[PDB]
Image (cartoon, rainbow, N blue to C red):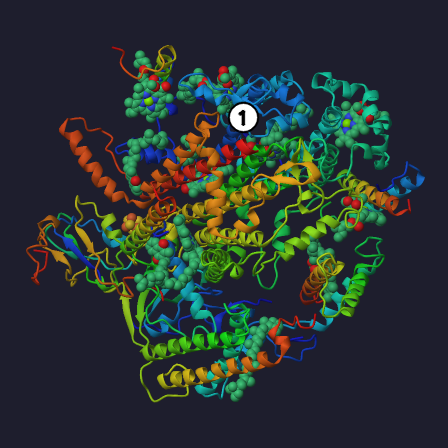
Amino acid sequence: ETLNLQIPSPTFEGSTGGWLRAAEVEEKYAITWTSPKEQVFEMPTGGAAIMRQGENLLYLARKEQCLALATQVKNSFKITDYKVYRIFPSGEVQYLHPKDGVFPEKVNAGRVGVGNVSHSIGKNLNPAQIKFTSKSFNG
Amino acid sequence: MFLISWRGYWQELIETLVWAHERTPLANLVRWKDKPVALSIVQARLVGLIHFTAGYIFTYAAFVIASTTGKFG
Amino acid sequence: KKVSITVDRDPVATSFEKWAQPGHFSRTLAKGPKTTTWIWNLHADVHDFDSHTNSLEDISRKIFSAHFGQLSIIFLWLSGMYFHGARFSNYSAWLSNPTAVKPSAQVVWPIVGQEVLNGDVGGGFQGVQVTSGFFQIWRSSGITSEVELYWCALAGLIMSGLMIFAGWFHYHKAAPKLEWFQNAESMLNHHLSGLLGLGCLSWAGHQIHVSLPVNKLLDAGVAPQEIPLPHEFLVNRDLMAQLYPSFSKGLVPFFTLNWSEYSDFLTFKGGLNPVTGGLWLSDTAHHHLALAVLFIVAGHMYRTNWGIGHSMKEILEAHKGPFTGEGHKGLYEILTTSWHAQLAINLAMLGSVSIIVAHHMYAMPPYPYIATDYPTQLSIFTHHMWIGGFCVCGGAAHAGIFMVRDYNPAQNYNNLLDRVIRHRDAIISHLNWICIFLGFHSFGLYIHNDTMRALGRTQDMFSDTAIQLKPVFAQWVQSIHTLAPGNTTPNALATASYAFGGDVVAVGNKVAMMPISLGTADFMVHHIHAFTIHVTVLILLKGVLFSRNSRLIPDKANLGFRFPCDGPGRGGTCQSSAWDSVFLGLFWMYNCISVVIFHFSWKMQSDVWGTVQSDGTVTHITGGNFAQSAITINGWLRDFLWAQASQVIQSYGSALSAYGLIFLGAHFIWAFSLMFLFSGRGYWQELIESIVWAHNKLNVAPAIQPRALSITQGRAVGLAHYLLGGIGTTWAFFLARIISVG
Amino acid sequence: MDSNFLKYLSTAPVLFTVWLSFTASFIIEANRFFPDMLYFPM
Amino acid sequence: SHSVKVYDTCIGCTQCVRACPCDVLEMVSWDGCKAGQIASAPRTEDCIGCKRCETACPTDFLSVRVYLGGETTRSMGLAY
Amino acid sequence: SQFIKPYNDDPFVGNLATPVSTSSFTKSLLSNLPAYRAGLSPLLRGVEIGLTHGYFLVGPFYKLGPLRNSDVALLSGFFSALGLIVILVACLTIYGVVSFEETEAKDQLQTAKGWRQFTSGWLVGSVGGASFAYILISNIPFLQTAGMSML
Amino acid sequence: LSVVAQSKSDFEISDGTPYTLNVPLVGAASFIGWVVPTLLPSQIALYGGKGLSTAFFASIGTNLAKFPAPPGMTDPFWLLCFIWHSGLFATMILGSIGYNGYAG
Amino acid sequence: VPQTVAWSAKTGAVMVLSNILCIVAGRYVIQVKSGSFAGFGLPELLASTSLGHIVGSGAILGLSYVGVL
Ligand code: CLA
Ligand code: CLA
Ligand code: CLA
Ligand code: CLA
Ligand code: CLA
Ligand SMILES: CC1=CCCC(C)(C)[C@H]1/C=C/C(C)=C/C=C/C(C)=C/C=C/C=C(C)/C=C/C=C(C)/C=C/C1=C(C)CCCC1(C)C
Ligand SMILES: CC1=C(C/C=C(\C)CCC[C@H](C)CCC[C@H](C)CCCC(C)C)C(=O)c2ccccc2C1=O
Ligand SMILES: CC1=C(C/C=C(\C)CCC[C@H](C)CCC[C@H](C)CCCC(C)C)C(=O)c2ccccc2C1=O
Ligand code: SF4
């Protein structure tokens, strides 16, 4: 499951759009995927890179940069074998996406609903009733 | 400037300046405690309104006092 | 023979059916309106051909026929300028007395008291004074009568009909295939050799056989109706020899290479004609002939159908060094498959050429009696500076559309585009620093001077009297150009322009041209120019370079060229598109060109234009106040805007009352624009809800549901009315001022 | 006359331009024959 | 962080989940609607506040509602 | 041959290895500057940086200040340099107070004690360099003009 | 002279790429290849009967005689200096391109 | 004004020389087409003679300028 750090990266000539000091002191994100070919893609941070046949690995500063590349590869090259990780400066690696092996738009058992409100949006509480009270406006 | 130009432009400028500070020798020894960001949407509306209003007041005050003093009538 | 003509016959049927179906060209709009946004969406995207069609062939066909339609409009416009000169003008009176009669080719009808605009322009005529310089063009052409202006108007009408026919024919009857349009070598060969070279050559023939004899007779003092008709110069060589004796030898000196025989009419005089204050037409004839040879030679460079010539792709692919990766590889494919990339280049070039035209025409006045018609000189400078600034911003607009749409990284691996995008942070950070440094050290000098002058410390100012900022490099270049005749241009007789130094040229007791000296004020306003040009480049370059993705929005290319925002998140991403940098950069273009035309207007009135008097001294229009008053902002406010707005604001009840009204009308429109620029759509949609309620109450609600304009359209309406009001106010101020005093 | 060309002349911008040009034209004609009507003459 | 709510008017069209650029939303099982599924927001610490989910939603007033709240490095979209 | 490569072998860091950034000449200059030179205590780094900055600060104040045409121009220029020095030392001290946690390490610039040492050295060297510039300009008529004494 | 033609120094044009700047050969060859054609005389008031290199060198000596005083705005020194160094830099650029790149 | 000369056999000489020069030199340099009897056709002849009248006209005018004639 865990990120094999030794995976070769896509060939790239470098750019100024990559990650900065906050990546090595706050968090960095990684994306891995399998390619059937040695083909050109566009980096979220800049110009063009070439993905190597087999397994690829990138490091990006934002999670959204990892997911923007993931949508681009899925539509352009029909690759869905992408895994997104969060990596902390302690060395600890956090698997992120897809979170339980199944993509979020496909249903899965054992997913518990978070954020679900039992009434429609117009049935919320007016601000005055919950003033100087800790009670939430969602009913 | 605060009322016509909006946030997305300025945030992309500030990101090029953050890069330049981090890459410039003898200057990257000095670090911000707070990450430089563009002003918020509401804050920029307020900053432009304050500048507009202050310019309105100062211009008219100079005219109404100086024209009356200079003319005396 | 791979360069060949290939045509589809009868592609599109000439039918009125799609005229009756507005929105037929796109799948979204063709199903009809449901909200008022559809109406705006109909006009906004209509000439965006590559958003309706996928195929490059149909796009190319639509563009070719739309270019014929534009040519038809230009020919009709030219025909109307010639017809109004023939029928409603005092051109004949102007030819007899140029330095007294004021050109006028527009007469108003008497309806609501508006016939006050038919002022006394002179020559027994009443009309609106015109400042386009057509009279001087016609006199340089050798027109000399209204009848020939009627024939020119008819020639324009015939050409206009031929262009609108050709656009119809080449879209509906005979439309070329894509492989015809993708012939860049053939097109360049014909447009350099054929369009430019033959055009220059044919004009040189007209100047030698028609313009030069008629204008020599006019400047000798012969009356216009006493001058022989232009074809008697063509047939009787004896009269042409009497004017210029080299014509006695004919074309034998041309073919035997004994070209110094033709020095009567092919000169290199330089300077100005003393009689008219214009360029020597013998110089312009030699100039056009020299250009024609160079353009025709240039036209033989590229390879078309016989093995001689260059491959443009090979030239581009060979230029690559150690800093730049694969080099210019892949640029040929871009520039023959993307119309937007070509329009980006050609708009930047057309705008640059229009700014060069603006500079070169006041400094080396080409037409007879145009240098002392000061309303025309101010008008044609201001007009070509505005056309230049607009076209330059459209080059960055279509560079952004190229990057968002036509750019594909697979064909652009490690070439020059890929490398620019991969160090765009270094480019924009260094440009940003230059714009900050140059705003501090240009405009802060003005703020320093306002503060010192206000404090009573005139010795602490940046001025000629006090601390001096001297434009030593420009003064030195002026020295070189004044020393050039007989030295580094040995066969020149005079300087290229008297602006660099030399004599005062006076025509009709008015200065044509005289040296434009540079001091501390000139140093300061030139660095103001460098600052405003730099930041305008930064806004447009930042828009083109970050059009596809940023650190802010990693997938900006999927949203397109023109989107309003990507939501209030990430702190707020309002105005993040490439379109919004064109939107913001047209304001800075407006700022730049406004200071350029103000600098020109004040400097020419203060130090160049005026009346020569006894003892050879010259009294200028504003009496040389530029040097000591263009160094503070208060000087520009008082001695330029306030002092020279006297003529526009006192114009009521005269023939210039139209400028007085347009001054106020444009002040109004400008202010009205800030309603659209400072406001947001959500307020106006909620206000429209209550107005819709009042219509619902009376059962008169429309079936096309009213909407507030989109976020992008709100920005576009604000920018359009801002540009109209600001430029219109300057137009009214400039024209009333210079018609009254110049 | 062709019904599709008449349907084009029935489109909103054409009718708007024709109707207000006609409107403008009879205001212009009324102020030509009867100018400076500051008041209803009575 | 931003607070994202899903109200029971959700028809289970999955459009918000496909539109979300930061993987905040996912589909869970629910018998309330015909589609048998409702959106859920388990990962709101990653919400940047783009409101692309709200744009995608087809119910009359949005079943998904984003309430912009406290800002973080994640919700500011800062790569520095 | 290519002169632009990924920074420190890493293609995904936000920098490039360009001749200005990483040539031998650049690395020699950067490695030998007092901020980065090896074997220097932070106080000595402060002294060398201060001597340099204090020395050039005197000149613009003296030549272009309000009292430049007076005979107290050099006095006013030195004292103006001193005022700027005191304000900048206040800026350095407050940066140190808010940017570094208190730890025993004192031989690096980016530590609390190392920053306090650098600030101490920078103030001493800066006043020293300004004083040296004052002495040189006071005594040598070439420096009082722009070299204009020779003409 | 940050690196000569011989493989002696370790000067790397960038992080990891060693590149021999041929500062002696390029400077010498570009100087001679620019100065020798420029010896062509011309009876123009700027040149005064000399070539551009020789009139330039003459104007260096003339202004060095009046050592503290700078040459004036109308003095031929500035125009000679500009054109000379313009063509010299162009010939160094083209020479460095030709020698480093084509290597023969 | 630079001094040009009426046509003489020396002018003819310069024209002929430049013309032959451009034939031979063009024959080698041209990249798309028995030293002159392989692949020599009318467009190559017409191009080399067009460059011949260009080089020849420049040579005639320059040699007339300097006094060589
Ligand atoms: C192309 C540029 C151009 C411009 C800007 C002008 C401008 C002018 N001309 Mg000139 N003119 C031109 C070309 C031009 N002309 C040409 C090419 C000719 C030669 C044929 C003339 C011949 C000419 C004459 C003979 C006269 C003018 C006059 C005038 C003035 C008043 C025109 C007017 O109010 O009539 C308005 C006339 C109307 C019939 C009103 C028509 C309004 C309609 C409704 C416009 C609608 C367009 C339509 C809806 C488009 C869509 C088509 C449809 C199928 C939907 C005005 C200054 C007059 C003048 O100077 O008097 C002193 C005058 O008498 N012009
Ligand atoms: C000698 C050949 C020749 C000439 C003169 C032109 C001229 C022109 N082309 Mg080009 N073109 C050529 C060959 C030529 N083309 C070839 C071979 C191709 C195929 C590769 C193209 C493909 C091409 C495209 C795809 C487009 C053009 C366009 C244009 C117009 C540019 C806009 C402009 O400045 O017009 C204004 C200037 C003028 C001088 C107007 C002149 C109008 C006529 C047509 C000029 C020639 C008349 C005739 C030869 C003169 C007879 C003289 C006689 C009285 C003695 C201009 C008319 C553009 C355009 O606007 O299309 C309409 C455009 O989009 N051309
Ligand atoms: C040769 C010139 C040229 C050409 C062919 C094009 C062509 C195009 N441009 Mg480009 N552009 C140009 C110049 C040009 N532009 C210049 C000079 C600028 C700088 C301002 C731009 C800025 C620009 C932007 C920012 C955009 C385009 C877009 C487009 C496309 C859509 C056009 C459309 O449907 O508009 C329809 C036309 C209109 C709606 C006309 C209304 C425009 C103004 C408000 C009316 C004019 C006012 C009038 C002159 C004065 C009124 C008088 C007053 C007193 C009453 C098309 C590919 C758009 C696009 O998305 O393409 C992909 C787009 O967003 N262009
Ligand atoms: C008078 C109005 C005004 C002013 C001063 C500015 C100022 C600026 N704009 Mg803005 N702008 C304006 C109107 C204005 N804009 C409008 C109306 C728009 C609408 C479209 C924009 C849109 C816009 C964009 C899109 C861009 C700018 C940019 C810039 C900067 C240019 C760089 C520069 O000159 O730095 C130097 C600063 C100045 C010249 C400001 C005046 C400072 C003087 C010297 C006095 C300083 C006093 C001093 C600090 C006092 C200290 C003590 C005090 C604190 C007590 C600068 C911050 C660009 C930018 O940021 O790039 C760098 C940029 O991209 N502006
Ligand atoms: C100004 C002097 C000059 C010029 C014009 C050239 C030109 C050329 N050299 Mg040479 N070279 C020079 C100085 C110069 N070199 C010196 C000083 C050295 C020694 C250090 C060399 C050593 C050298 C070698 C070892 C080789 C060349 C080669 C070449 C050719 C192609 C490669 C190149 O440099 O592209 C330059 C490309 C062009 C000049 C043509 C492009 C046309 C544009 C308009 C360029 C103009 C640039 C500039 C404005 C011209 C300035 C001229 C003058 C006023 C200074 C080209 C003919 C190579 C070759 O092909 O072998 C023969 C090769 O192997 N050169
Ligand atoms: C030239 C050049 C050419 C090529 C390009 C280039 C590199 C950009 C450019 C360089 C330009 C630049 C940037 C040149 C920069 C040059 C600079 C800034 C030189 C600074 C010198 C400082 C001195 C001499 C301080 C001396 C202090 C002393 C002796 C101490 C005295 C005191 C102490 C404490 C001890 C007690 C007594 C007192 C008197 C109190
Ligand atoms: C210029 C500009 C910026 C950039 C402006 C910034 C980053 C402000 C930075 C100014 C300096 C750093 C501090 C300002 C200091 C003031 C003189 C006042 C200081 C505080 C006093 C009240 C005490 C935006 O971020 C922005 C965002 C949204 C819409 C429009 C705009 C906009 O127009
Ligand atoms: C007034 C205003 C509106 C409302 C404006 C509307 C609904 C325009 C409707 C005006 C009428 C319906 C048409 C205007 C016609 C005029 C007579 C001029 C026509 C000009 C050409 C288009 C014909 C917005 O929608 C808006 C949106 C975003 C920022 C600012 C604003 C804003 O300021
Ligand atoms: S304000 Fe208007 S533009 Fe800025 S984000 Fe909210 S919606 Fe998009």
Q: Horizontal and vertical percent for residue F73?
A: 53, 73
For residue F137, side relative to residue C18 (left or right): right
Question: What amino acid is found at the position of numbered circle 1 in the picture?
Answer: Gln
Q: Horizontal and vertical percent for residue G39?
A: 83, 61
For residue F42, side relative to residue E38 (left or right): right
* Local crowd size for mark 1, using a 10 Å CA cut-off: few (<14), some (14–19), many (≥20): many
Residue at x-position 43% and y-position 52% = C543
Q: Horizontal and vertical percent for residue C366?
A: 66, 35
Residue at x-position 45% and y-position 27% = C657
For residue C518, side relative to residue F35 (left or right): right
Q: Of residues C711 and F24, which is closer to you in this image?
A: C711
Quadrant of the frame with the C terminus of chain C: top right
Q: Of residues D36 and A4, which is closer to you in this image?
A: D36
For residue C549, side relative to residue C521 (left or right): left
Q: Would you name the residue on which mark 1 appears?
A: C129
Evaluate whether residue F85 shows in this view.
yes
